[PDB]
Image (cartoon, rainbow over all chains, first blue to last red):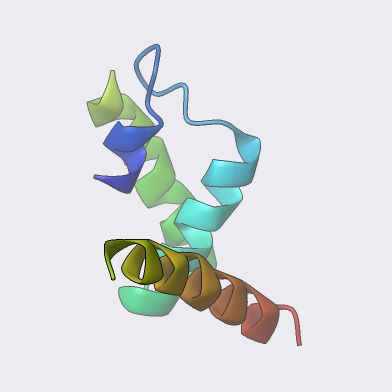
Length: 48
Length: 22
């Protein structure tokens, strides 16, 4: 939802929101850092 | 009170990001 709020043109959630997204994933989901950036990549993939 | 709730959201995001950068 926090992706979809700022999503604009597909996965056009920007760089600040991408580091904030991966940080939240790494905090709430306890998902490792490269996997949190990966779940960003999957987030933008689905956000399209 | 709805304004306070949205304000709480901003404050909690700031606190979590500051805890990340500390």
